[PDB]
Structure formats: C-alpha cells, structure tokens
Length: 288
Image (cartoon, rainbow, N blue to C red; front, side, top):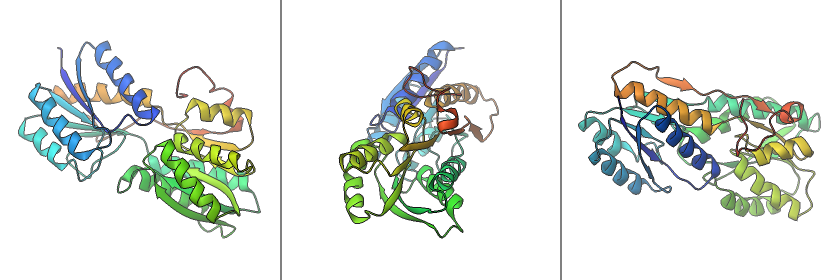
C-alpha cells in the first residue's frame, strides 16, 4: 500500500553502514515503498535535525541507527508527536522503540573470545582491545562477551583500549600507541573487522605478524585473511545485508499497526579457518 519509510543512518564512515544503507534502499524498493534517507555522519545534532526533516516529508515510520542512545531522545519525542513509531537497527536505544532489529552482540563477543582462548593455547597472553562507540551498548556487549570467555583464565589478560568508532583510520592511530606500550602483546581484538585490519597493518609494519587478530563482522577482506593466512584468526558474522532487509520489512509492519517482536535477531556465527573458505565471495560482507 506504498509506505513512506524514513531511515536515519548513524554514519557512512565504515563499509558496514554503507552496505546496510544499500540493503535498506533495495528492500524498500522491492516491496514497492519509498525510502526517505539521511546520513548523520556521526553527528548527534545532524541526526536530530535530519529526523525532523524526514518527519516533515511525511514518513509513516522511522528507522534509526542512533548515533548516541541518549542524544537521540529528541527524535523519539518528535516521532511520537508525529504519530509514528520507531524501529532501531544495529544500535539499540534504552527505550521508546517499537522494535530493535539487530544481533546479540554479547554472544558475538563471546564467540570471538572462545576462538581467542583456543588459539592462544596454554601460553595464553596479553590481548589489546580496540573498541567501537563510547556509551553505546553494541560496544559494551562485544567487550563483555569477549571478556566473559576469557574470565577465570589468568594466563590471559586484556588491555582495554579506546573507542575508535568502528573507523579503521582511528584504530590505526590507537594501535601505534598501544603496540609501543605493550610489546609483549600476543593478540588484538577489535570490535569490528574494519578496525581489526587497521590494527593488522600496524602490526605488519612493525614485523609483528605473530600477533593474532580478532574481529567482528565478516568483512570479506577479513574472511579472506582468515582463510589465506595465520594472523587473522576469527570473526563473527554481522551481515548488514540481512539486517537491512529485516529492518525495512519490520518497519513496514509497524507502519501498518502490526505487532512485531521487540527484538528481531538477524543471526550470527563464528568465522575461523575451519569454515572461512566456504564464505569467500565477491560481496563486501560474507553471509550465511
């Protein structure tokens, strides 16, 4: 019945968000609906301004990837005053969304952490951790999940590094400071593959291919390195493509007054050597 679907994206500064946007555009068109789209470029005030703009264009429902879980509270208010519902995608809000279309980020962090335990073996070792969004639950859960997997294992220690916002360039900067400060490093866990591969370049420039690398997402470049080398060990699947389709399908139901679950889980799974070969392909991200 031709819906107007609003989509406020948080950023486009890493390939995940670009693919998520593209998948969302294609799903809206496939079901014959109009996608009104804005990218906040990592900026809270731009996001809340963009949401008002979308509301003015008459969206029937708002899909949002919050730049910040409390910073978006004005857009939630604006949505309600407009008589429309809100669907979060990828990053949750505390409350106020009809549905969250995402993944169990703790369980992904746990998945990866178990791969680290197994790989690091009995020597264990120090792991440097490079994180995503400060104050957001996606980063908190990927941290806590990973931690849960190595806790009670004193031969492993974690160095909690900074929040580099899922951006490779920023993780490069952090890996330098951290490499020099912790040369006894045996492992690096980044909360996405984009950042992990930035860390990996810095390691290679300093001849530390011996340091194992752990990520999240199933970025094809990461999957290829897992398949074809020994340094990049594991990641967890976080297909933006499937997430985008589920976000738009879920928003179409909402806009029409249908009941949807509060959490739509777009599914995940471990990528390591044992199965990376089957996931190599042409797209930007691997998928089940």
